[PDB]
Length: 190
RNA sequence: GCUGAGAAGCAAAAGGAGGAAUCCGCCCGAGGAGGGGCUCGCGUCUGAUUAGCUAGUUGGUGAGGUAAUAGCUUACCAAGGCG
Image (cartoon, rainbow, N blue to C red; front, top):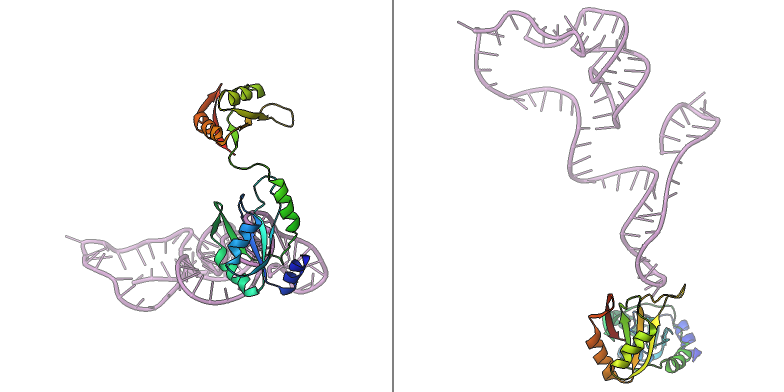
């Protein structure tokens, strides 16, 4: 498999470099988007997928220099996933990729807008308060305030996870505007 | 590069965008185009019921000054200069 990277190195311009790859964007959708241009032997996505979201830097490797020139030209201004990818050239591409794909497959745990992100919670707001909110509304899994690490005041940020996607949607829509005491909270699915 | 006969000395910099590639820059020079600053020949209204004017005035040197020549400015010398 390191054969694919070494083959590309040897060729010289099988290389094409992909910048601002989205958060949902994956080795397979990189391959599908770029295989139209020509037969990709290999595709490299860097591992920032702790969660779904990506590093937004990757490599693709062609059979030919010419396919790589065509993909560099055509792909730039391509929307994937709501974010737009430039293909200028890369260094001769680097397909650890098998390791990354395995970690990506493992790493992704959370699927679908099932968690709610809290914006604006006032500094008085307690972890228990968030439990009260989340439990009062549609039925509930867990509650967190993101508190300052340096020393540990709320910094007013925080999360729910609910038991259903529907409860997430209702909490987002019902809440946003929301006073909780002293300050106007915004909640989105994340 | 500059000052100076040479001797000698003196003088500059800035990072930013981008994964890179590179691009926009910055500092010191050398040209060019264009834009300016000066100088001069010639042309540029009437009145003699206005006939003398001009003393930094017109020259010269020295010292300064200007982006640059220059009474541009100043001290001294010459008495010029316009009609």
